[PDB]
Amino acid sequence: GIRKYKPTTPGRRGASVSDFAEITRSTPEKSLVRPLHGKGGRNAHGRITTRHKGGGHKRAYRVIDFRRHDKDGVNAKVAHIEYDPNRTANIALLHYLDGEKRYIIAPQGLKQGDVIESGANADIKPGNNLPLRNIPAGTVIHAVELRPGGGAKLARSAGVSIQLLGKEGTYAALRMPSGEIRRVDVRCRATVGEVGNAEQSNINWGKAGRMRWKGKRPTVRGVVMNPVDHPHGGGEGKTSGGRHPVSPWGKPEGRTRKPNKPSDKLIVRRRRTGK
Amino acid sequence: KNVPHGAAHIKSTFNNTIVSITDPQGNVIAWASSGHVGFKGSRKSTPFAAQLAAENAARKAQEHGVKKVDVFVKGPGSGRETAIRSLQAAGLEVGTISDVTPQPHNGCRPPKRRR
Amino acid sequence: LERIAEHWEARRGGVPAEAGREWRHESEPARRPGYFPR
Amino acid sequence: TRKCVFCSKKGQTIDYKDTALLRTYISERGKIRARRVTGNCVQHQRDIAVAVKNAREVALLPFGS
Amino acid sequence: GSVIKKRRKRMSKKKHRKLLRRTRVQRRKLG
Amino acid sequence: ALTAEQKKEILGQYGLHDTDTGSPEAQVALLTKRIQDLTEHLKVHKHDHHSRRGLLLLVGRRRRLLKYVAQVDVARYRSLIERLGLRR
Amino acid sequence: MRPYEIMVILDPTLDERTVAPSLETFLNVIRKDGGTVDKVDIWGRRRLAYEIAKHAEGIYAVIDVKAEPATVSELDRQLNLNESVLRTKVLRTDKH
RNA sequence: GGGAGACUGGAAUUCCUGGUGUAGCGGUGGAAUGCGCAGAUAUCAGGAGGAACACCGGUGGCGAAGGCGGGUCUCUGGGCAGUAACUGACGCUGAGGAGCGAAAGCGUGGGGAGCGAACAGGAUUAGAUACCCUGGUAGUCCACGCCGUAAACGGUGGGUACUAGGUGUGGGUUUCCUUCCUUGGGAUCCGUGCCGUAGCUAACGCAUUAAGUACCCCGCCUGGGGAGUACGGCCGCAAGG
C-alpha cells in the first residue's frame, strides 16, 4: 500500500513511500542475480543519446522468466515475493517440483504458498501461463508475447492488465493498456491476472533527492536556453518560445509512428486522446 | 432484380413517417419519405403525407417486381393506419401486420419534461 | 399593456397543449370509437 | 372473484422448470399477468414472478416474444 | 401557513448568500 | 444468529441449572457469542451499517443485564466477567 | 451440507452420448470434497427461447447435489470455464 | 425491495465495421441553428461500452430515520404468531455524548452510454443573461474518505392504560357451517387504510394508528422586522454548518 510521511521536514511534507506489504523476503536469490552497471544515458560512442540519466543507486539484475515454455505440466509453489529495483512490479520466486527456482513478475493477489501451473492443461487461476488458444475470451491477462516464442513483451508494468476480447482464425484480438486494440497469434502465451503493486503510481516523491536516487538528472526547459542551444531559446525576459513548440532538434509535434509499418495490418484501432 | 415477396417497414414518429420496402433478407429496395413527396416542417406529420409516402414507396417497389408484402409498423401513432391502407390501395397485398416498437426494460435516462 | 400583449410569448402558457393533460376549454376532445372499449 | 389455485389442497408447487405451468400465467406478449386477473395470493404471485424470471434467464421462456 | 413567510425568509437567505459569494477572497485574506 | 447446537453447548456451560435459558448468565453468554460473531462479520463488511445497529442493540442489552447482575450480587458479576473475558 | 439444484445448458454440437460421462468427471469435485451426493438427470436437445452464444439449440441437464457452499462454487466456477457449457444456474432447494 | 459482497441476464440508447439504399433527416405552436449528399435518416448482420432494471408492481411489503424491488449464491440485522420451558421488575425516558443520515457539493484514483448545471449557437421578445430547439463540460456511475444539511413532513417526541362501531387490506394462530374444494363464517394476536360516535378544537378537522381521558421523562415557544445575521468560539480541505 501507501504510507504517508509526516511533515517533519520541508522535504517530507507531501511525500509518501511504498508500503512494502507483499514483500516476504529482503534479499534476492543468489543464483538468479546478474551484475548491472549504469550507462549514464550514453551509447557505444560515449555520447549522451538519452538525456536526464546518470547517478542513482547501484542495482543488480534478477533474471525474470518471461519465456515460461519448458515447465509445461510441472507445478510450482510460490516461495517468496521480493522487491525488484529494475521494474515497477514485484517478483515472485517459484519452486518447481523438479527442483528449479525461477522468477516471474508477481500477479495481483498472488500469495506465498500458492500453486502455479503452466501449459494447455492449466487452470485459469492468476499466475498460470498457457497459450492464448486455451484462455477463454473476456478474461484479464498480462505478460503477453508478440510472436510465438519471443517471450512476454506486453502488459508488464505494475497494475497493468490486458483484456482478451475474442479469437477468430489464428488471431486473438486484445485491448492494450493504452486502449489500443491489436491482433496477435493464438500460439502466443500469456499469464492470467493483473500485475500487482497497482498503487505504486500514487507515490509522492517529495524532494529532488529521491529522483536523483532513482537516476534522473534535472531537466532544463528549452525557453531558458540560448538560441544556439534550443529552438525555443532566446529573447529578453520570459517568452513562450516565439514559435510553434518543437523538440531540441527542431522536429515539430505530431505523429511520429512510421507510416506503412509491417504491423499496421495487425492493429485494429490505435489509442485515442481527448475523449 | 425480381423479388416477388418483400417486407415493408413503416416508422411513424411525431413529426415524420418513413416507408422503406425491404427484401426479406433486410436489404432496402425502395424507400419514400414524408418530406420526399413535397411536404416540409410541421406539414409532414399529417396522415395525408404518410398516405402519399406509402403510396409512392408502394409504386417504387411495384415496378421492381414486389407483389406480396408483410408490414412491420413502428413508432408513436400518427399515420400508421393510413400508411397501411395506402399500401393496400396502391396495388400491394398486405399479408401480416406486426407492431415492433422498441420497448426498453427501463434502461436509459429520458430527456427532461418540456414546459 | 403587459396584460394586453397577445403575441406568442404572451399566450404560450395558455395554449391548451398539455397532450392528454391539463383539461382546458379549448383542449382537443378525445377521439372515441363507436364501440365500447371492454 | 377468482380462485388462487395454489392455496388449494391440490396446489401444485411452483417451479422454474415446469414451463407450461408458467406459460398459463404470462400473456401472449410474454409479460407477467397481474395479480387481479390471476387471483392468486401475494406470496404465490411473488413465487410466480420469480419463477418466470428464472425461466427467462435459462432461455425456457421468451424475453417478450 | 402562507408561503409569504417562506418567501421573506428565502429572500433574506438568498441576499446573504450573494453577499458571502461577493466577499470570499476579502474574508479569506482578512481572516 | 447462532444455531441450536452452539446455543445448547453455551447454555450447558453457563446455565445455572440444566434447564434455565433466561438467567442473566445464560443471556449474557449468548449475547457475548452473538457479538463476537457479528464483530467478525463486520470486520469484512465495513459498510453494513444496518447490521451494526443490531450489534449496538445487543451491546446495550448485555450492558443492562450485567448491571442487573452487579446490583443483585457482586460475586456473580465478578465471576461472570472473569469467565467471559470482559472488561467492565 | 445444503441441497442445491444445478441446471446447465451444453451446446448442441457435441454428441449426447458423451454428456453423461463428461458431467460425471465434472462432479468429481463435489464427490471427493466432503462425502457429497448427486442425482444427475439429462433431458437435452431442446430449442432455446432466444439465441445463446450463436446457438438456438441446447442440451439441458439438471443436477441435484448436496454439498458445502464452498464446494458448489468451485464446481460452478469450473463449469463456466469449460467451453462446452453455454450457461449454468445454481439454486438452493431449501426453503430459500 | 432490511443490509453488505461476489458473480451474472435481457430489452433499449449510443458509437464502430460491412451490406442494401437513396435524397433528405432532425426539430417546433411555427421555424432556424444542426446532421447528410465525402452517401445521412431508414433497413439488415456483427462488435464495444456504460447506466437503469419494463410486465410482476398497489396507496402492497420491509426498515429507527434517510430509504429499499433483473437473477443467483455467500454473510448478516430486525419483526410477528404459538407453546409458555426459563430469569424474576432486570422497566421507561434521557441533559450532555456517540453513531447513522436523501440530493447537491469536496478530495484521491477509475469510468463515462444516456441525461445534463455552466457554456455555445437558433428562435421568441421592445429587451431575452429564461421558458422552446441543436450541441454540450462538470456532475450523475465505482472504490475509499469528507460534508452533516431538506417541505429530513403525518409540518403530530418516546412509553403506558382506558374510551361506540362499520368496512377494506397484509402476516399468523384457532372453533363451527362443511362441500371441507371456498375471502365459508366466527374468535384472537400483530400491522396498514377509509368512514364515522362520545370527547376535543378558533376553525379546519382528529377521532382505538387521537389532535379524547390520564401518568412518567425529554426537546422547544414567549409580537413582527433587524436575524438564524454580526462578534467570539467549535467543527470542516473548502463550500459552509
Image: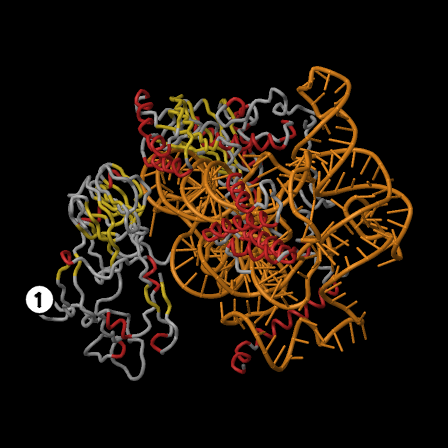
| Above-or-below relation of F12 to E14 | above
Give the quarter of the image for residue G3. Answer: top left
Q: Residue H33: x, y in percent?
A: 48, 56
Which one is in front, H198 or H120? H198
The crowd level at tag 1 (other Cα within 10 Å; few <14, some 14-19, many 20+) is: few
Q: Residue furthest left?
A: A45
For the residue labelled by badge 1, is the local secondary structure a helix, a strand or a loop?
loop
Q: Is residue B94 visible?
A: no
Residue, x 15% and y 68% (percent of image)? Answer: A38
Q: How many circles with numbers are drawn on the protein?
A: 1
Q: In which quarter of the image is the C terminus of chain A?
A: bottom left
Q: Residue G33: x, y in percent?
A: 35, 34
Q: Quadrant of the N terminus of chain A?
A: bottom left
| Above-or-below relation of A236 to B55 | below
Q: Can residue G51 be seen in this view?
A: yes
Q: Residue B115: x, y in percent?
A: 62, 52
Give the quarter of the image for residue A187. Answer: top left
How are the colours assigned in the image?
Answer: secondary structure
Which one is in front, H99 or B26? H99
Q: Residue F38: x, y in percent?
A: 51, 50
Which one is in front, D11 or B95? D11
Q: Please give the residue where the numbered disc 1 appears in the rendered image.
A: A44
For mark 1, name the chain: A
Which one is in front, A78 or H36? A78
Q: Which amino acid does label 1 sit on?
A: Ala
Q: Is residue A245 left or right of residue B2?
A: left
Q: Which residue lies furthest to the bottom in this view?
A: A236
| Above-or-below relation of H147 to F81 | below
